[PDB]
Amino acid sequence: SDPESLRWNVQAELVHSRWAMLGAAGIFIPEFLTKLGILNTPSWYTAGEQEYFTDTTTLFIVELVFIGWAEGRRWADILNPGCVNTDPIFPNNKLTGTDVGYPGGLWFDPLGWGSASPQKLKELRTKEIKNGRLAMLAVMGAWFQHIYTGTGPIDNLFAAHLADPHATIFAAFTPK
Amino acid sequence: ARAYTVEFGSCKFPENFTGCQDLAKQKKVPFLSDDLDLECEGKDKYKCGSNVFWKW
Amino acid sequence: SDPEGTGGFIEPKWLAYGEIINGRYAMLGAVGAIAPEILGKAGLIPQETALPWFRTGFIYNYWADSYTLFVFEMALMGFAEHRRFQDWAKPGSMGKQYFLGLEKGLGGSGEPAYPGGPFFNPLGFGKDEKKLKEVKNGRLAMLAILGYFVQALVTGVGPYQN
Amino acid sequence: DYIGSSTNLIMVTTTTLMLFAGRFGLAPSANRKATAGLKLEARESGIQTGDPAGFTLADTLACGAVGHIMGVGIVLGLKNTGVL
Amino acid sequence: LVDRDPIKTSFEQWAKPGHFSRTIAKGPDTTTWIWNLHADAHDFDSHTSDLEEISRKVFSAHFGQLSIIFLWLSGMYFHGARFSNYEAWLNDPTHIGPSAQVVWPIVGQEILNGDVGGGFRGIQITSGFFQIWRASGITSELQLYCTAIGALVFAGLMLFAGWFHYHKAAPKLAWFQDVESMLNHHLAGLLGLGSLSWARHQVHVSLPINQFLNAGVDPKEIPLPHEFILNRDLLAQLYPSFAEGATPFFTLNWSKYADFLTFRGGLDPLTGGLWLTDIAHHHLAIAILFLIAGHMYRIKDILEAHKGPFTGQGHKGLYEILTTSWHAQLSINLAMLGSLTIVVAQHMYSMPPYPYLATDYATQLSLFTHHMWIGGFLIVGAAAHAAIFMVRDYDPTTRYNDLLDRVLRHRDAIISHLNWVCIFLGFHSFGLYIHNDTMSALGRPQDMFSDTAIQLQPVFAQWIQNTHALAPGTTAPGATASTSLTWGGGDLVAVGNKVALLPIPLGTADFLVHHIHAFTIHVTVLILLKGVLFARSSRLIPDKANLGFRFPCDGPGRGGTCQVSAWDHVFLGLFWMYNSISVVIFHFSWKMQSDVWGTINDQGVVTHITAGNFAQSSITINGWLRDFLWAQASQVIQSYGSSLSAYGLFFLGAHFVWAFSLMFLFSGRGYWQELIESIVWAHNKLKVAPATQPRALSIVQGRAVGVTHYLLGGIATTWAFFLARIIAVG
Ligand code: CLA
Ligand code: CLA
Ligand SMILES: CC(=CC=C/C(C)=C/C=C/C=C(C)/C=C/C=C(C)/C=C/C1=C(C)CCCC1(C)C)/C=C/C1=C(C)CCCC1(C)C
Ligand SMILES: CC(=CC=C/C(C)=C/C=C/C=C(C)/C=C/C=C(C)/C=C/C1=C(C)CCCC1(C)C)/C=C/C1=C(C)CCCC1(C)C
Ligand SMILES: CC(=CC=C/C(C)=C/C=C/C=C(C)\C=C\C=C(C)\C=C\C1=C(C)CCCC1(C)C)/C=C/C1=C(C)CCCC1(C)C
Ligand SMILES: CC1=C(C/C=C(\C)CCC[C@H](C)CCC[C@@H](C)CCCC(C)C)C(=O)c2ccccc2C1=O
Ligand SMILES: OC[C@H]1O[C@](CO)(O[C@H]2O[C@H](CO)[C@@H](O)[C@H](O)[C@H]2O)[C@@H](O)[C@@H]1O
């Protein structure tokens, strides 16, 4: 008859989805773009030629210092200031709420018409393919399985085996 | 690629074809052939009673 | 809103009337007798490892029309059975036509059940000549009949009758 | 078939022995105990005629009437009746 | 209740303090209601004053047992599969010593995992799968791995039938409140159509697939996954394809046969699990009945019928309200279900029904005491719930002047007798032993009660045992041995690893245990009988059905006025039964090993786990810790650093937990209050307590945390004491 489920912060999950899959937009075409044999072959002897490696897990700091700065300072001030204490405007804070941010403060505001509104027209682009990313990297992020799993010979683990026709990997297409 | 063309025999016709490899004819006429021998014949006609259950 | 599923004395019977109607032409074997010269038998597990039924039928089970891509069918075209079950909930616009071009009077039928758009070509009777659960009733009296005919044997013995 | 064909008819020798001896034994029921050999409605003797038990329990012997010798110690004598 | 009846919300009740009687859990904070809530969670004097639902809940929240028994069993079939030892053990029984469970070597663990058979580290078993499992007209590890998910199938589905009740808008009255048919169905075709169906998959497949196992092979050098169809050609070795018969009847000739069955009795030399050539026939010969039987019938009629002079006028009418009770038609059941479980516990040990049991000692006595504590833990219950009837269930008093209104009529009476019964027993039923001590410690045997001093003379024999093993010469047809090999007459040769069953002799030291049982079974029942009987009214309190069947104790007056009630008669009646069963167990193994279990070798000079020490020496009730408790148990208190060790290492806890019960059992109540405040004080100074008024235990909760502990203590104590003296010699 139906679940009392809609989170109220059901509003948050979705701008958490603009995260996961717009971000995963920068994966589908850089990966499956490849360039097969551009001319041919990658040769990467450069910042990794001969200086005792380069990254790996000093990669993580240099990667996620300013991604720490990027992601960190994102949802914190997407909009919300005011931020204090006592009573509810319902999500699980909304202490900004009725207050935009500052009474008579500065230029807290982006743009005219007493709001944060970047006008009403732009439902066209970011509704379809951009949240399509959600429903695309859903099964095309679940091509993950098909692309590698089956562990190209080398490794069978707790040998049950249980079947044998032929291998499985990735390249595009398929037998049949 | 025995049978890229399951080609086989006569054409035609008289009898036990299935050579000669294959063989035989084993019980022949409508049988086997079925396969599909062919055809249907004023027989015989299978149905019961006979073959004269020739055994013995 | 949440999808629906009304039980009421006897939906189970309208869709149960229907289930057998579909199975009455999925009866197949004697409704379309050209269908199986020998196709009623599926032909399981007769590897070039091994064996079929047992003494069978044996003069696999068969030559074959094989394969895989068997689930994807019954699923994907089952991904249609529940569409002529939604689309024609109605508000019609199915004929999206084509943006431009006034030349598209061309119709096809309408909603069809039977000789088509309508019935059609009015004009009829000379010769063909001389209630619709009966168009049901008799084909379970065709369905459940092959049912025992799969195992239709006494084997050790045979027709006592005879 | 086989002797089991003369035994196909012997489905009758039990099932018809059972079910034909059926209705009567449940017919004038709503009765429980009781009959004639006890409490009030006397007409004595043993008597004569009153069915199921009598006839069909005698028919198990009957099935062994004509098939007798038959099977038994197979055929003997020169026509036991004397008639040609 | 309140928010927000009735038509107007879906919107579910998550948030707003309380529910469960009406100046309910009150706004005002407290703790007691958190044992409330769980306790009495199921109950019915609240939910609604109207039957209706309740049967609409119990037919659902029932369901989730089957489903569970079903998630369970799966993790046991899976377990009895890929955590293998079953494959290994079967080609190799007499030899193995089975496992299913194994640790993972985290922290101390591993000691628990100690070479068990077909070559691996693990912890043993006394739960005879690996032996139902003989069955497998097939064998294969991944196979049980289908039977297994076949399990999780029945579950999810036989667990969405419980959605597909209460939560779905439910049936009603008539549906159960017409009873007219119920057992018609149940016993006919399931009781029947199982045992029946079990027949078909008990010679088809199983019989043959251990007809030629009882010899050698290594499986799949036998029993394919289909093989057993139309092929009625291997069914050729284990009798005809009926040859010339047609659907039994008689115009049949046997010049040399008589279908499978050909009735056994005794025990396979090579697998003494009793014969299977029978096991079909007996299940077949069941079902028929059930098949014929479940065909009554429609109800009163039969009980509305036979009355008499002193007999039961109310017999006639023995309950409209037996379609309107539950608490009644549950309590009846428990006495049977329960009393019909520990009848298992015998026919098992003196007639094994699975291949490899007896030889397997420890893997069927575990059984005979597990099955033994249900045929008791379900019986005191079977009384409790009658008390629950006797107090409340019906609306008013519409039930009148009958079999009961009768029994009660006498009541200071049926229980007036029964009492003296017990002190007659007890004096003839325990101080009997105490004689011995006082006079064997005085020491003059001339005059003990020995199986030899007080007049009885080197024979027990002439009674009924000796007319059981010897009865295959009555109306009896026959079939070499008896019915149960443990009977007086004839035969010996049973098994080629260790032993199994043989006669089992008696007299005294069998005579008098058998009597302590009487007095123990009796005074148990006294307290439950008088308990449930005096349920609602009495001449210590008549105003005494006025709350419920619990209530702590009426009040300091009348002298005592404490225990009374019948929660509590079903509190001191557990207290006994824990003995009832706890000493019956003590009986079986001291016998079954003092004699029986022991062992063959040349000239089959029998060598019991103990040369019958029993003899002259259980008769002394010290001998019961000279010969028992101090003798055996030397395996519990040696058990450190081993593989089983988890027993010795329990046997201290749980032999602690019990010795923690007394604190819950033996103490006041405004005590731990008076204490709980000193505490509550020190709490407030730092500012750390008040919210949720911390409170002591609810007089009768206190008794709830006696008892339950006293048992899960005093019990697993032996569950340990045991598995530690059959694993390892015995
Ligand atoms: C590998 C297997 C083989 C097998 C065993 C099956 C089995 C099945 N297929 Mg199928 N199929 C196969 C190959 C196979 N298919 C192939 C190679 C194709 C590609 C064309 C299809 C395409 C296909 C479609 C589109 C559908 C099926 C459907 C089905 C199911 C329909 C049952 C039925 O009796 O409908 C027929 C029986 C009747 C009584 C209906 C009568 C209607 C007839 C008169 C219309 C077609 C006859 C027509 C006039 C012939 C003209 C030629 C035309 C084909 C160009 C059935 C389980 C159907 C389904 O089950 O959907 C949920 C449907 O989905 N199949
Ligand atoms: C067919 C049987 C069965 C059923 C369906 C019921 C059903 C019911 N019984 Mg009942 N009962 C039964 C058998 C049954 N009983 C038996 C065999 C006995 C004898 C012991 C009893 C003795 C009994 C009493 C005394 C009472 C009931 C009551 C009830 C009602 C309360 C249910 C409740 O809240 O759960 C209660 C369960 C809990 C609150 C869970 C606590 C369980 C603890 C003690 C754990 C047990 C030890 C175990 C080893 C711990 C787990 C392991 C741990 C170490 C990790 C309910 C209608 C009560 C009532 O007031 O009637 C309306 C009343 O209390 N029963
Ligand atoms: C044997 C084989 C095969 C195959 C193939 C295959 C074959 C593959 C497979 C695949 C699979 C899949 C894709 C899946 C599956 C699944 C299944 C099959 C299942 C089933 C079942 C059952 C059985 C019952 C229950 C249900 C279920 C579903 C579980 C082979 C054979 C051969 C020979 C003679 C020689 C060499 C060559 C070849 C030709 C090689
Ligand atoms: C559906 C069915 C069935 C069946 C069958 C069945 C339905 C069977 C069943 C059986 C049952 C059983 C066999 C039971 C079991 C139980 C158990 C096993 C348990 C045990 C135990 C105990 C002892 C107590 C508690 C615990 C436990 C649980 C462990 C069928 C149906 C039908 C129809 C209509 C159509 C045609 C065909 C037929 C067939 C005619
Ligand atoms: C001290 C302890 C413990 C002890 C313990 C002991 C010292 C004892 C215990 C016991 C328990 C028990 C005991 C339970 C259980 C169980 C079971 C599982 C059972 C089962 C069974 C059955 C089934 C029925 C009857 C029989 C038997 C018992 C076998 C602990 C402590 C602690 C600390 C420091 C702090 C934190 C927390 C902890 C960590 C906690
Ligand atoms: C000892 C004893 C007590 C005192 C026992 C008490 C107070 C036990 C209750 C203690 C509770 C269970 C502790 C609960 C606290 C924790 C659940 C809170 C923290 C949560 C966890 C994370 C630890 C009684 O109240 C009593 C009442 C009636 C008869 C006999 C006795 C009796 O013998
Ligand atoms: O064009 C269909 C194709 O199938 C035909 C019909 O054309 O008929 C049999 O052959 C196919 C294989 O192609 C079978 O699967 C089909 O279901 C059969 O009726 C055959 O003539 C064609 O090849």
Image: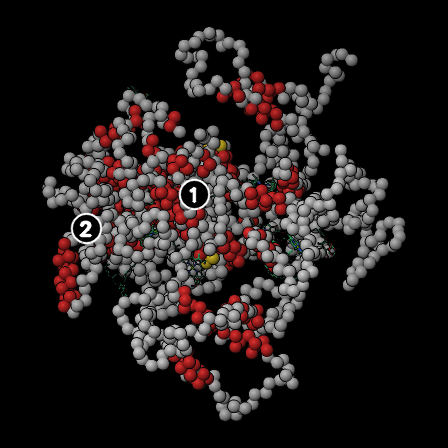
Q: Chain of mark 2?
A: E
Q: Residues within 10 Å of mark 2 (few under 14, many from 20)?
A: some
Q: Is residue C141 left or right of residue E678?
A: right
How many numbered circles are shown?
2
Circle 1 residue:
E351
**What is the secondary structure assignment of the residue under circle 2?**
loop
Q: Is residue E678 above or below residue B34?
A: below
Residue E450 placed where, x, y %? 26, 42
Find out if the beta carbon at label 1 lies less than 8 Å from the nearest ligand 4 atom: no
Residue E674 placed where, x, y %? 13, 58
Q: Is residue E286 left or right of residue D65?
A: left
**What is the secondary structure assignment of the residue under circle 1?**
loop
* Three-letter code for the amino acid on which mark 2 is drawn: Ile
Circle 2 residue:
E699
- C-beta proximity under 8 Å, tags 1 and 2: no
Residue drawn at x 47%, y 86% is A55
Look at the image and tell me whether residue E203 can be seen.
no
Residue C125 placed where, x, y %? 75, 38
Label 1 and label 2: CA atoms lie apart by 47 Å
Q: Chain of mark 1?
A: E
Residue drawn at x 43%, y 18% is D31
- Looking at the rendered structure, whether the residues under marks 1 and 2 are on a common chain is answered as yes
Q: Residues within 10 Å of mark 1 (few under 14, many from 20)?
A: many
Find out if the beta carbon at label 2 lies less than 8 Å from the nearest ligand 6 atom: yes
Q: Is residue E132 above or below residue E491?
A: below
Look at the image and tell me whether residue A83 can be seen.
yes
Q: Is residue E457 left or right of residue A12?
A: left
- Dividing the picture into quadrants, the one containing residue E490 is top left
